[PDB]
Image (cartoon, rainbow, N blue to C red):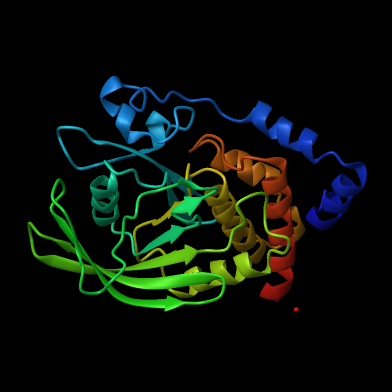
Amino acid sequence: MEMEKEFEQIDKSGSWAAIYQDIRHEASDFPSRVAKLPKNKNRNRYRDVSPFDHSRIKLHQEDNDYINASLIKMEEAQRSYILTQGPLPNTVGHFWEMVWEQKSRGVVMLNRVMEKGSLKCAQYWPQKEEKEMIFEDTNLKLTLISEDIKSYYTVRQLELENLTTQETREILHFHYTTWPDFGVPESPASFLNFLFKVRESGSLSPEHGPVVVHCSAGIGRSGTFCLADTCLLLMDKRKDPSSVDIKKVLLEMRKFRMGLIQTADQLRFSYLAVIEGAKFIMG
């Protein structure tokens, strides 16, 4: 079926939970043996969220190459994304090592450091220009260059220096700051505006390594971001845009990381975002 009318048909019939459970039943199951080794317990935020072995990002290190991060490679859309958990106190150096080694331009953050009164990720970037951060375990230096605070999101320019080689690179930090503590946003308008700002920066483009996107677990809000981006790109590429099947795209993405889209409300919100976004792309 088309999307917008499949949408109203699920609303009127109140069957979002049944649609979402079908997706959960059909989703791929692949091994995640490296994530479960005892030496990696303090590298995982949640025991039930792990990268598959076949798609995990490897650190260029011989001691321990493990990080909770997955490469999502979308062949027809010609887009790739790295989805990862919010960094932990003992993985902030690994996080920036990955950004460096994978040649990423942009980092997309969809959570606040504290939500619901608890810490959802480490304070992994500097908050003042004159107070830079040094990660001694991976030999990197990170400096805040500039910060632009808007009503729904903040964009930061950061300088990452590899202290071994003295090479430097400019990284863009895109921080969506207004996702509610409970539920999903009422309108997708600010989320879509944010997506377009990431796109306009070059961070999603083939001349750079894959964008790094995270929330707390790296599957819920993060899944919504890449699902909406890929579906809108396919609608532009194909002769028949009504042939884009959001459930099929999501199942394809779940071949590369488990659990993408965590609730039936997140599924409904993803439909809403693609529907509204397809009108703005053209009128």
